[PDB]
Every structure is written in structure tokens, then in C-alpha cells.
Length: 129
Ligand SMILES: [Au+]
Ligand SMILES: [Cl-]
Ligand SMILES: [Cl-]
Ligand SMILES: [Cl-]
Image (cartoon, rainbow, N blue to C red; front, top):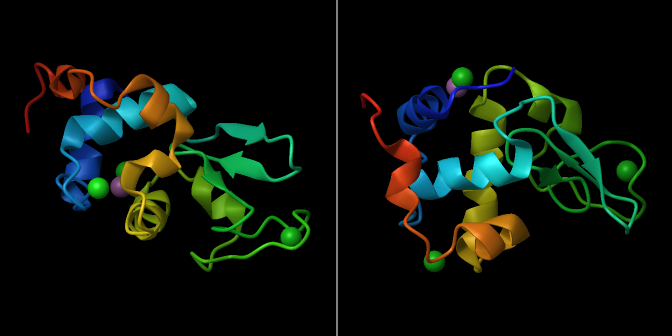
């Protein structure tokens, strides 16, 4: 599913992601933007042979199982394909565990590169939450 900007922002809230580990909601929406352009079915291979899955490009090297990433963990105890659902509970459960990993949102290279320090509130502009 391709979520609307406000649509995702509200789903993320209801799921507790907003101010999670102290990252304000527009940090998340910003991250989802640049990782997946809001598309839950987004998949992307990395040079190391692992793949990133879904709305937040959760990586099969440590977080989920895809059956093809050699030497890999499944910290979120889920098959990577559940990270492609239209309901984002699974990706969000997993992202909670990733951002609690010690480096916060830096774990999303794209967040650090494109959202970190910018005016994130702009991503939840005009939304009814
Ligand atoms: Au959801
Ligand atoms: Cl594997
Ligand atoms: Cl949802
Ligand atoms: Cl932090």
C-alpha cells in the first residue's frame, strides 16, 4: 500500500511511534518518506546481499528473516515478508526494537542523511492528529 503522508502519520501515532525513544512523529514520517516513499511493498537489496523490507526498509541482516541473507539474525523474530503488509504493526514493532539499539534513528542511513536536523514537523503539517 502507498500511504498518504497524513495517513501514515496517524497510523504511526496510534501505534505509539510518536516520541518513541524521543523521536517526534515527523521524524518517522520523514524517515518512511525517504526509505520507501510511503510504499509498504518497497524492497531493496544492499551490496552486502541483505535486503531492506517495507515502509522503513528494515534490513534482513539483523532484524528479519528472508532465507537468503547468510550469517544473519532475526532480532524482530519475523519473516521479512510480514514487513510488507498494509497494516504496519509489524514494521513498527520492529522499528521500536531498532531505534532502541543505541544509535537511535541513525540506524536509518537515509534519516541521518536527509531528515536529521531538518524541520521534521513539516512532514506532519496540516494533519488531523
Ligand atoms: Au497500523
Ligand atoms: Cl537467511
Ligand atoms: Cl496501518
Ligand atoms: Cl537518541
